[PDB]
Length: 48
Length: 49
Image (tube, rainbow over all chains, first blue to last red; front, side, top):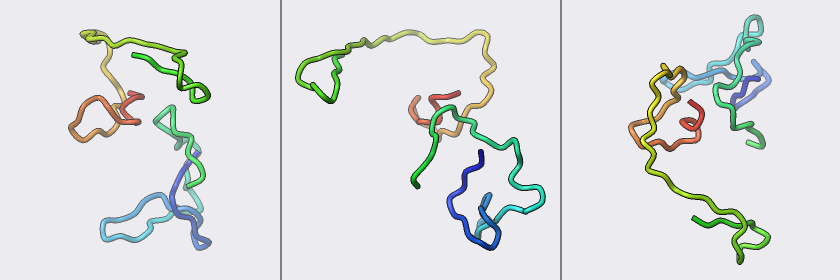
């Protein structure tokens, strides 16, 4: 259910970024949540 | 207003209309408005609401 743009091998997928830009990744323990999905019914994203 | 299919755009298949309907909602407190800057009722997000 979760979608993020970049994925590297160090921490998997990111979940956001800070202001002075750097990829703020996901914790292996409690991220990504099982419940985070889409608030829009459309836009099944893919290929980018 | 007049539409058609991409196979035959020469001859119109489907048509439709346009309406100045005074849309209101006396009973919706409108949870989940998505982000629009300031504009009209046009974004792919604002179509959900």
